[PDB]
Image (spheres, coloured by chain):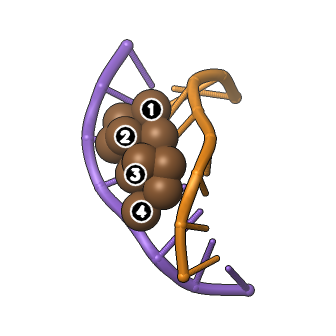
Chain colours: A brown, B orange, C purple
Amino acid sequence: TXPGVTXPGV
DNA sequence: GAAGCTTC
DNA sequence: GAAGCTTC
């Protein structure tokens, strides 16, 4: 997730 | 080490 | 199997 905590996604 | 799910 | 990097 994020970043941080990508997306999700990407 | 945990923290981090939603896509292609 | 690849695709997403940054936080705590």
Mark 4 vs mark 3, CA separation in Å: 5 Å
Q: Which residue is mark 2?
A: A2
On the same chain, marks 4 and 3? The answer is yes
Contact flag, marks 4 and 1 (Cβ < 8 Å): no
Contact flag, marks 2 and 1 (Cβ < 8 Å): yes
| Chain holding disc 4 | A
Q: Amino acid at mark 3?
A: Thr
Contact flag, marks 4 and 3 (Cβ < 8 Å): yes
| Chain holding disc 2 | A
On the same chain, marks 3 and 2? The answer is yes
Circle 1 Cα neighbour tier, 10 Å, few/some/many (<14 / 14–19 / ≥20): few
On the same chain, marks 2 and 1? The answer is yes
| Chain holding disc 3 | A
- Residue depicted at 42% across the width and 48% down the height: A7
Q: Which residue is mark 1?
A: A5
Q: Which residue is mark 4?
A: A10
Q: Amino acid at mark 1?
A: Val
Q: Quadrant of the C terminus of chain A?
A: bottom left
Q: Earlier in the sequence, mark 4 or mark 2?
A: 2
Contact flag, marks 3 and 2 (Cβ < 8 Å): yes
- Residue depicted at 37% across the width and 40% down the height: A2
Circle 2 Cα neighbour tier, 10 Å, few/some/many (<14 / 14–19 / ≥20): few
Circle 4 Cα neighbour tier, 10 Å, few/some/many (<14 / 14–19 / ≥20): few
Mark 2 vs mark 1, CA separation in Å: 5 Å
Q: Which residue is mark 3?
A: A6
Residue B6 x, y percent position in the rendering: 58, 51
Q: Secondary structure at mark 2?
A: loop
